Amino acid sequence: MDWGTLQTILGGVNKHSTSIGK
Image (cartoon, rainbow, N blue to C red):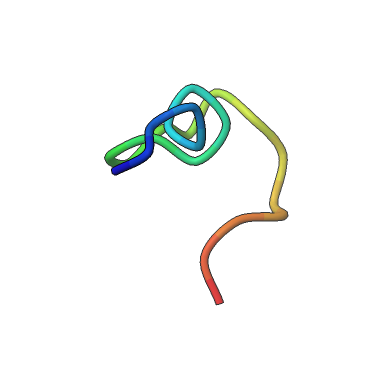
C-alpha cells in the first residue's frame, strides 16, 4: 500500500476526526 497512508487512513482507523474516506 506504499504504506504510510495507513496510520493516517489505516485499514479503518477511527481514532481521528472526520476527514477520511471519500
